[PDB]
Amino acid sequence: GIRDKGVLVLAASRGIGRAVADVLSQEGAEVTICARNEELLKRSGHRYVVCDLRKDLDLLFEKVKEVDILVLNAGGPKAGFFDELTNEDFKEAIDSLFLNMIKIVRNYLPAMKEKGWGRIVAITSFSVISPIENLYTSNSARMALTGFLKTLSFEVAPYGITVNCVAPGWTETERVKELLSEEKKKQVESQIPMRRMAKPEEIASVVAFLCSEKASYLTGQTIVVDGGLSKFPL
Amino acid sequence: GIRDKGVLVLAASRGIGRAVADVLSQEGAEVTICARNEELLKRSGHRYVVCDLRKDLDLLFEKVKEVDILVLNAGGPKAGFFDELTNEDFKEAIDSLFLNMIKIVRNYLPAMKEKGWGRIVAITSFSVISPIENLYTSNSARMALTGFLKTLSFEVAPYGITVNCVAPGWTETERVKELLSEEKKKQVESQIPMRRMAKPEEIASVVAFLCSEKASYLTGQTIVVDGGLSKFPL
Amino acid sequence: GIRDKGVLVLAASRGIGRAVADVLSQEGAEVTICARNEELLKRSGHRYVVCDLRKDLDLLFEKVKEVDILVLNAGGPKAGFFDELTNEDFKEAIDSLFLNMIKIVRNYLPAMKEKGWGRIVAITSFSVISPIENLYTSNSARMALTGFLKTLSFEVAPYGITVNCVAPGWTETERVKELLSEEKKKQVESQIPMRRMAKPEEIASVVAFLCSEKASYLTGQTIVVDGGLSKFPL
Amino acid sequence: GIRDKGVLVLAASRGIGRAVADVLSQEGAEVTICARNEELLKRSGHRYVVCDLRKDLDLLFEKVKEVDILVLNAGGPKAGFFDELTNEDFKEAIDSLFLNMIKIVRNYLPAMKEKGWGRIVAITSFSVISPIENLYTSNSARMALTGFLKTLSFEVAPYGITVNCVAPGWTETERVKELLSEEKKKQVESQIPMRRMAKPEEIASVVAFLCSEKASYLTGQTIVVDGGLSKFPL
């Protein structure tokens, strides 16, 4: 039940974030998205803020004041094996996937406490429980955030705020339909039990559910939505 | 989207299984429940079969022929420390919570393959990831079923059938409001971050979601719905 | 420090169980092994008892009275897709890999409590956290025993008894060098980061360490020994 | 078998790090320890470097050139609930427990590859799988490092290098015998199944084992050494 709730979705001009904004809009929430590309944002049909999170967080906090539902999401950082990654690559990933996210929570959390209701949902990756061999930066940075949000979930629970992650597997975002060949996309598709990648709305729907009033007893969890790919049984 | 899908819910005259039946009925599914007590079943307002998961299941298969959605559920076996449990206690738990469930899946799975759609959802316990010290029989039997359903999820994924568990924490079922004093209830309730037990419908709605067309890319997963109690971070 | 401790190792005429028996013997423990094949046992150079892990229980308890260290181990049950496995397959695996093990523990446990010192070690499989797709019977039965032992580990901890599993990955036992071609062997080997299967002693040495006095604060854990194969981060 | 291997242990003038250096010295390794406190280090009887690792990595790499075995370890960061922690608290923890650690590995890893043998062991905490409610900064930073090392273990495995964490539970270090009252110590002690905290050597021996030639097929693992405290069963 999310008619009239305030929603912010980060990195939401395209891909999963976009799909999440779309759903929540169709279920009557008042949604703001934010991203780097203004042109993409004007075309989205949503309320938007142009927001490079490294440089200018106070612009975001000024233009989007309070928020019942917060979906954390980011671009994926550099892939590579250990010798082709610098200290700067790990630092940038930590800043943008972990420390900047903490700042954003810290900002919007007090109004949720005051209302006695809230939702935080972080979009991470199934690579969190089934680490991919060349994603050193995002593996470790998403484990970081996932730990932070678990510890958080304990403290905010009594205020009616849930805190969860959704860990999508391979998703057919326009970004992925460019980072990969047809040969590589087939090979990967063939190791997914469902023998396909997710439509972005298939990830969106899980996130929309955790945001609804029906998910009120579910917190401190990472829901993996990956077609059956990861092997971990519990 | 589950108007007109055939649904069977086990151990569903009371508690969580009852709530699950109620929801899916409200969303337009054709629901049959089954349990031991016929008088409870007559009063439930649902299609029913009298059935016992410690014994023969043939009556069940005859009276309920095909099924799009199958929710596995049972009564909780005996609690106890090791010296106050017999080999029989372990065997009865294994038969009822594991082997008889495999036989039920075996039975309704073929018609799901034939249609290219299906859903299997097992209601287990948060004790599976956060084992309670005197639940030796249910801990180990629920691990067994979880292990079985994960292995299964791999195989049936390409047929459009998902396989998941919902692992509820402390829930205010009539059964629990009788297993426990007031003193023990408050002690428990004070260790749950949400500071309360779940209404049965709070577990129901998660199950109901996994059963919908929206959960199409989510399989092989145990969703813990426990108010934040279990500490495991992934 | 295990000079003169009494040891029983199951399924130990060949493979990993044999390697465990040999180590513990070299470190001065008085070791009994047990298995079906009497001529293999005669030739092993160890104290032995002939036993099935189905019928022959109280012969074992008769000929092997008390034991400081108990290594549980069994043959691997039938591998297969769901439609090529019977109710009897699941039932035999649960009896031999789970309920018979509970019986053996129940037997040898009282004398460990009496002495204030004990060691139980179950050899299971890395398939426990990274389930292989057609090992339905072993996956679920090993999860069952792993769950049992974890719950157990809580209760026997104060009595100076540790309870742990060792989960070996692909090991070069002569059984495996027969279950597999050269082509299948290489395919598998090339997905192990160490690019090879374990010598049986490389699993044995882990088991031997859990059995030593030095492992005195480590209980309720499954050590995975798999050359890096399983993806699970925690 | 580690007679003559070169060993470096960080944060090792006291506590667990100290205990690890002691053992490995007794087994014939040539050990250097490093910490901030020079006077403690002189008194240790070991080879030592003094270093605030924010600013003396150049010193450390200079005075300790190559190393077969690398035990990563750090002081514990600030404990607190979310409102009493700043962005600098999170930053400092990430720096010191994660990004500095990567820099050290990056340094000592090439000579391990060149020799075809090595060991990296991080001492983390059982709070990684059983997160404590007010350790936001260490929980999330240790998850980061654990995720980093697991991703690394895949790549370095073919080179004869293992990568593991040891996650001690409550240990009777002098530092802990000061952070806690008697009253709080006993409450804690009474929730550990073993009913006591670890002697630092009891965590040291697990580390020493991972460092030996006998742990050759064991990598990509976090061994939890916690007297049975954490409930996670797998």
Image (cartoon, coloured by chain):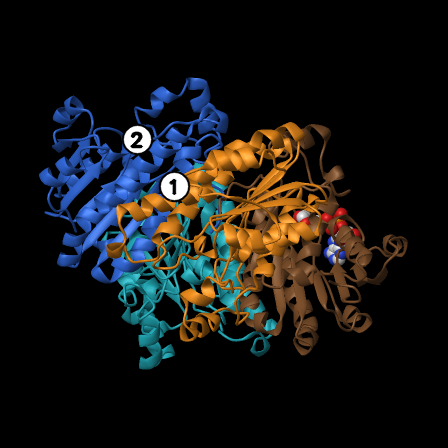
Chain colours: A orange, B brown, C cyan, D blue
Residue D218 drawn at (x, y percent): 30, 55
Residue B152 drawn at (x, y percent): 57, 68
Observer-nearest residue: B117 or C223? B117
Q: Secondary structure at mark 2?
A: loop
Report crowding for label 1: few under 14, some 14 to 19, many 20 or more residues within 10 A (C-alpha).
some
Tell whether D142 sits left or right of C55.
Answer: left
Observer-nearest residue: B64 or A68? A68
**Which numbered disc, 1 or 2, marks the residue closer to the eye?**
1
Residue A195 drawn at (x, y percent): 52, 72
Residue annotated with mark 2: D75
Q: Do tags 1 and 2 sit on the same chain?
A: no
What chain does badge 1 belong to? A
Q: CA distance from mark 1 to mark 2?
A: 22 Å
Residue C86 drawn at (x, y percent): 59, 75
Residue at left 51%, top 53%? A39
Q: Secondary structure at mark 1?
A: helix
What chain does badge 2 belong to? D
Report crowding for label 2: few under 14, some 14 to 19, many 20 or more residues within 10 A (C-alpha).
some
Q: Amino acid at mark 1?
A: Asp
Residue annotated with mark 1: A95
Observer-nearest residue: A22 or C47? A22
Residue at left 13%, top 32%? D48
Number of dots carrying numbers: 2
* The N terminus of chain C sits in image quarter: top left
Residue A43's quadrant in the figure? bottom right
Q: Amino acid at mark 2?
A: Gly
Tell whether C46 sits left or right of D141.
Answer: left
